[PDB]
Image (cartoon, grey):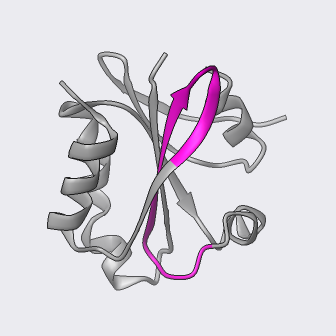
Amino acid sequence: SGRENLYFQGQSIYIELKNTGSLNQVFSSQNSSIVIKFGAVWCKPCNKIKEYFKNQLNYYYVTLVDIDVDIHPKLNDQHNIKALPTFEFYFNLNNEWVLVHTVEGANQNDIEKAFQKYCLEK
């Protein structure tokens, strides 16, 4: 039993994940690119790029998932997160989700290069 709030810009989607179990359900769908950002409320560089990350909906066909690692510590540990923020870029290839790149840190230039390489620009 759970609620999620989806924010749509065309077919692009942003979600600030409430329930750990809803992640499996996000992946159960129309955007080839899903990008997950792992961060935390107290984390200064996570906050510095938080608006930049959510605004990627305007620029990319993408489903964006925001994960507070202190709300979802299981997902933190399962994805082996070593620094905050961490960005995981997923692509659906041959009917399977594939982790295609990870970026650690809040350097916006580097994150943007990753979106350009691993995501689908509008």
Q: How far across and down, in percent of the image, does residue 35 sit?
A: 44, 46
Tally of marks: 0
Residue at 74% x, 72% y: name it.
77
Q: How far across and down, in percent of the image, does residue 49 sit?
A: 27, 66
Q: Is residue 90 magenta?
A: yes
Highlighted magenta segment, given as a residue range: 81-99
Q: From the viewer's perspective, is residue 110 above or below residue 106? A: above
- Among the 4 quarters of the image, the one containing residue 79: bottom right
Please identify the residue farthest to the front as the structure is shown. Answer: 94
Q: Is residue 22 left or right of residue 81?
A: right
Q: Is residue 114 left or right of residue 87?
A: left
Our reading of the magenta stretch's main secondary structure is: strand
Residue at 21% x, 66% y: name it.
110
Position of the C terminus, as image quadrant, is top left
Residue at 31% x, 47% y: name it.
54
Please identify the residue farthest to the right as the structure is shown. Answer: 1
For the residue pair 96 and 47, the one nearer the viewer reads as 96
Q: How far across and down, in percent of the image, does residue 10 sit?
A: 29, 16
